[PDB]
Image (cartoon, rainbow over the protein chains, first blue to last red):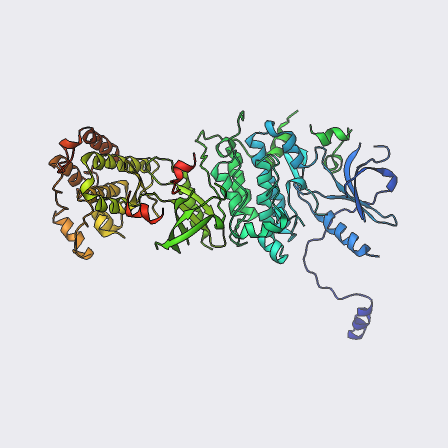
Length: 300
Length: 300
């Protein structure tokens, strides 16, 4: 049967087996034909707001990134398709035209920042607190996959429905950056916590601009002298205390996303105790385009 | 609409509501830039006497506590900002420099102990008795929030104006301690009453030192054999009787702050009957620095 000599020969035919027991990545990469989607507005190669429209079957909010250095575009695609979290946006598909194109989902109700500005007077404490939980949960999932977002902000969270938000794909914003990021270009999950802190502030102020009319060049110094974004009028000191902690100069002084989840959860369990909003007791983007069906809800 | 299945799903999006009806803590935590205040003298990480000086708008007496173990500094800040009483000092703000800094108010006329020494011959019974009411009222407020001061003393009361005093922030003094505190390190509101008793004595003696030149090591025994601080010459036995009661060995024998308020109130209503002072019928600290405007009076 199998002599030692024959066994060597087949080493040329069968690679030696060394099972890692690592989990197979079964993420789906859908290829989409160009005709199936239309571009409507330009958002930024370049990025278009557009709809995806499968032949026969529904119009789906998509962002289309049209950008050789194709190892780059395909590798980004790989990680973008791989994320599976209810609060993180997933790659829809790609289009392999001469200029390869990335298709990511956009939510029917737009970016959260626009949403709080429009719905300023009609947003109760429950909605705000639960959004923070969800944002932490998405960031925490990213921590677990060892992905640093590097640009978490209210404009980068999208409204799937009023009670569901998702962090939009990562593809320099001084006023959201950690001090170490500004000074030494260091980016870590703890630098992301600082950014989460700022974004929470944006929500609580209903879309105020951070550090308004202060030059970017000055932000670094203001931070070192210990000024931080001010307490929002609706925020009990309990809530505000969490924001502040996220802006400690020492990255390890800041809380972790797993901690933040627990903290904001407890608050969402009793929202009127932690946020005081007077009278507490669709959107412009939604009316722009508009079926206008979100991708998650269309597929799987 | 909302099936039971959908309702479960959203439990992942909306935390279950369980309203406590507890009062939201709306205390303000102000962040201050380092440039805005200067340190002048060292009082004690370390503590500096200094002024706070807002850009544009006033120079405010502040103590600056410059002290990782930042969960500690921030938690103390939380409770310090939360107190709202006319006779208890409140946190001014913090500064989030790499070494986090606490800023608490200091009164324009300094500590009460220095005040009675300087103004020894010009302090009538009215002033002394009303100060005691105010000290009880502050301690009583602390009782209500379930905060044990642990170091109430004349040096720890500050003169806002001659008719207004405030207990300075809590941030071992054997000669002011209760017997149980010395023996077993037990601290309670009733241990604070003993300390109030001693501090009242300091005022009535115009700043005499308690147990003078007796070793601390001996104080415990002297107490058990039933010696206590002597009757001050200006004190009727009525006043002195209250001090003595505060030094009962059994903590529950001692009066309560709510009782003390009533008692000293009655005396302040007729001061010449309870304190005999002959001729009854600014400061050094105030002249040190020196607008020199107290914080309460600057803000809200």
